[PDB]
Image (cartoon, rainbow, N blue to C red):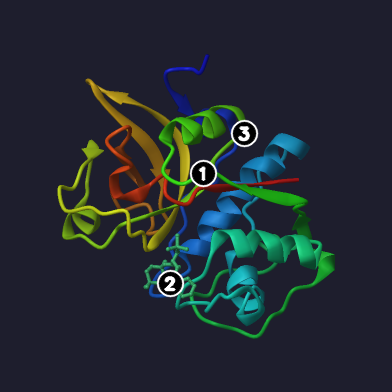
Amino acid sequence: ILPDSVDWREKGCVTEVKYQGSCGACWAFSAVGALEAQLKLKTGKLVSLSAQNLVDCSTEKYGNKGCNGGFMTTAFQYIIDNKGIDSDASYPYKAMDQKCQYDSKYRAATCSKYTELPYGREDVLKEAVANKGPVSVGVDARHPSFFLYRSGVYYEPSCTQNVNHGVLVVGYGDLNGKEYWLVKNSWGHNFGEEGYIRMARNKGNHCGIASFPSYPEI
Ligand SMILES: *C(#N)C1([N]C(=O)[C]([C][Si]([C])([C])[C])[N]C(=O)N2[C][C]O[C][C]2)[C][C]S(=O)(=O)[C][C]1
């Protein structure tokens, strides 16, 4: 039995909304966001993790291209292999590709593994968000409506399952009969509902939100 609605922000596991700027680091922010929640659950401290650390270090060997794109899963594996990721405070985001400057003396979190959910199963995604924590996902944000989104439950007739933008599901619920996923974006606090966007849930894997979900564990 799963709760009808969930919002991890109420549980203190979600940091402030970040602004990626002109650097395509959505994948990095999605990844640190998921781990930030696990760090809170494990240690009791809420700490923004270094997305820059990922942009700069989880590079070619992980199939990532810094400001030109990357994967949340391989980002998680990097943290695992690297035996750590620095805090955002010690390794600030500059919205540009830099030489890897990771240092274990600034480590703020570790990762032991990650789990990729089965393709397109929103019911499995719901279970993971309710019982595990925020889940990193990819969505189709290629449409004008996404950029122009301001409030309510987002539904785009032209959306596809071909995802291109990494975000973080921090909860779910329903708005007057319209079910949705509560999504934390990395386009600053001025985008959508102060950094967040509620996307159609249980509407045939709308915009591929349940296409490639994954979450890390400490
Ligand atoms: C973000 N910001 C952009 N996207 C990505 O990083 C996506 C994330 Si997913 C589809 C959920 C794995 N990844 C890529 O675009 N990759 C291409 C390069 O190799 C790694 C994966 C940044 C790139 S973008 O401007 O094309 C869209 C937004």
The part of the image, by quadrant, that contains residue 72 is bottom right
197 versus 56 height, above or below: above
Q: Residues within 10 Å of mark 2 (few under 14, many from 20)?
A: many
Q: Position of residue 56 (x, y in %)?
A: 62, 77
The structure residue drawn at horizontal position 37% and vertical position 59%, both measured from the top left corner, is 187
CA separation in Å, label 2 and label 1: 26 Å
**Residue with the mark numbered 3:** 132
Report if the beta carbon of the residue with label 2 is closer than 8 angstroms to ligand 1. Answer: yes
Q: Which mark is residue 24?
A: 2
List the single residue furthest toward the top.
Answer: 1
**Position of residue 164 in the picture relative to residue 107 (left or right):** left
CA separation in Å, label 3 and label 1: 15 Å
Q: Is residue 50 visible?
A: no
Q: Position of residue 175 (x, y in %)?
A: 26, 25
Please name the amino acid that badge 3 sits on. Answer: Lys
Which quadrant is home to the C terminus? top right
**Residue with the mark numbered 1:** 118
CA separation in Å, label 2 and label 3: 27 Å
Quadrant containing ligand 1: bottom left
Q: Position of residue 152 (x, y in %)?
A: 23, 36
Does label 2 or label 1 sit earlier along the sequence?
2
Q: Nearer the viewer, mark 3 or mark 1?
A: 1
Please name the amino acid that badge 2 sits on. Answer: Gly
166 versus 39 height, above or below: below
